[PDB]
Structures are given as structure tokens and as C-alpha cells.
Image (cartoon, rainbow over all chains, first blue to last red; front, side):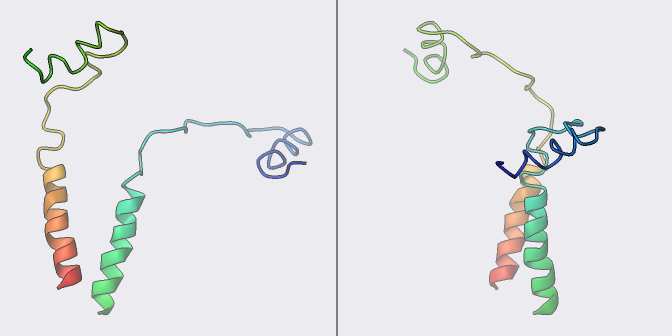
Length: 51
Length: 51
């Protein structure tokens, strides 16, 4: 010691206490992805939106 | 025998045981889509981000 956790818380716790431990949570996964999908999120969003 | 489942575980379971069976789961649806939406996800993301 040781420280861390332990110390942280425990120590404180102890011291003190309460809670610590736990809650619930642990493990589961939740995120893982979910936060990893967020990583692709900043990996495509600002890239295309700047390019 | 037979183987497958059976064997696977059962056988072982037996041997052994624990757990196986179951848990919771089954069915529901959851994904289916959901994994299918993931299929569109690789079907557009890397496509546009390479093109």
C-alpha cells in the first residue's frame, strides 16, 4: 546501554509511566504494497506531471 | 498417482502432519478485479512511464 529501543521509552517509562508498550499493531502486510503503491504513486505522478 | 494436489501435501501430510487443508479461503471475488486492476496497473504504468 545499549541505546536504541532500550532507552527509548523504557528508560523514561521507568522515569515516568504511561503507554510505552503496544497498541494494536504487529505484523500484517497492511501496507506491504500500500505504501509501496504510494511509492509507485510518487514514482509516476510527479514524474509524468513534471515531464 | 495421480500427482498434483494428491501428492502435494496429502502424501507428506500422511508422512508428516500439520496445516495442510484450509485456512479462511475459498471463493469470494476478492481480487476478481483487484489483481486484474493490478494487471491494468502494469498495463498503463510502465507503458506510459517508458513511452
